[PDB]
Image (cartoon, helix red, strand yellow):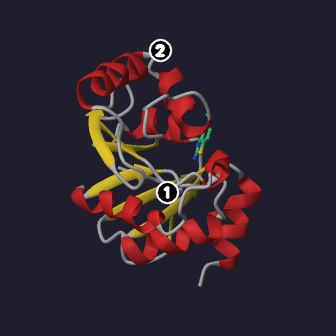
Amino acid sequence: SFSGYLKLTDNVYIKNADIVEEAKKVKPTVVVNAANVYLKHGGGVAGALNKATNNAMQVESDDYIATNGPLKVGGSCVLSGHNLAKHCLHVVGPNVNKGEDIQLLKSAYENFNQHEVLLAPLLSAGIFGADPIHSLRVCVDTVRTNVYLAVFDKNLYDKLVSSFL
Ligand SMILES: COc1ccc2sc(N)nc2c1
């Protein structure tokens, strides 16, 4: 199963890891993508997960958007996990660099509660512009299922662990 994680709470675990390398190693039931409403996996976690699937995630996502239209900010959809996981849960956290309501981060994390165990990044962190310390706090206060958080940046990982209440 998941190895090398630091236990933060009863159900939240954290590791300094590349979520792509982590997914290829574990091949979890669910890997969470830090998606946008259009499922355009250009950069950040989305660009990295999509590149690991040789663009199969983007091809599948474009067909999903053509049929269903865009997701809502705070919403999600379950698609294939390709070579990384059984499924990919594409979750849209608010992008504060696009003026989206940070209050939607709790709604975004509520999507994780539909899955018993997930490999995930911190929602709205990185290129989404939110404070990762706040994202971790919303994660532990919202997610009740088993969430294994992969934090790419060692210095951010240390700051998250050392400041965790
Ligand atoms: C390989 O690129 C990336 C980019 C962002 C993230 S967040 C995370 N935990 N792992 C990654 C890996």
Q: Which mark is residue 54?
A: 2
Asked if residue 76 lies left or right of residue 58, the reply is left
Asked if residue 119 lies left or right of residue 20, the reply is left
User: Quadrant location of the C terminus?
Assistant: bottom right
User: How far is disc 1 from disc 2 in space, using C-alphas?
Assistant: 24 Å
Q: Quadrant of residue 27?
A: top left
Kind of residue at badge 2: Asn
**Quick check: 134 above or below 46?**
below
Residue 146 screen position, x and y as percent: 33, 63
Q: Earlier in the sequence, mark 1 or mark 2?
A: 2
Kind of residue at badge 1: Leu
Q: Which mark is residue 149?
A: 1
Label 1 lies in ligand 1 vicinity (Cβ under 8 Å): yes
Write the residue at 47% across / 14% down: 54
Tell me whether circle 1 and circle 2 mark residues in contact (CB < 8 Å).
no
Assign a secondary structure to mark 2: loop
